[PDB]
Image (cartoon, rainbow, N blue to C red; front, side, top):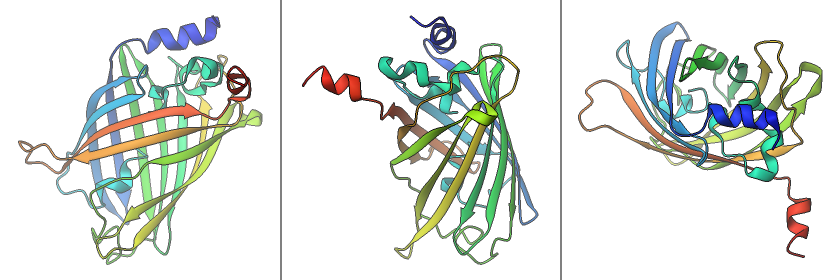
Length: 239
């Protein structure tokens, strides 16, 4: 229909292999994470297994879920002209976040998301500062679980990209919650054209599990992301 959505969508037809690379440093605790799996953007479906290749992960796995490929979001047909993430491919986009853990430290992340051949690669640098060595993060007090969210995507026309801020609440074992306030910006890597979206949101669902045969520190993630929020015309079709 739109030759630009055709280009982006053609890159994400079928199952696409995914590689995630994360080099991390939180309060000087250095670590690396490697992730492998596949994404099926027609269903907004991600199946990823992450391993800490440097030993024990010094932060809880749930705190890294958002950092560790929104181009696999399912954009329904009536919204596909608002899919910035795929429109930037194959050259990719830069995704930058600051994640403020309330009453604790913050992560600062910079990632390049792009195709290397048929593989969608998410290459991340994470820097965390001002964490409490006995707090919920460095103290590993967070439940190994995750919640569904609705994050609002806004155009950032000045930067020919998008931005978003949203709150994630990690369950603490004692029963409280640890707030992680996300500030996000995405900008295309090359000088090619992109689709700048109307305001909309992404609805997420994530299941974390363990591989019984994996002796390394790891996370299995089953995640679905669907776009929504531009429905004036569609709603009228049904009076």
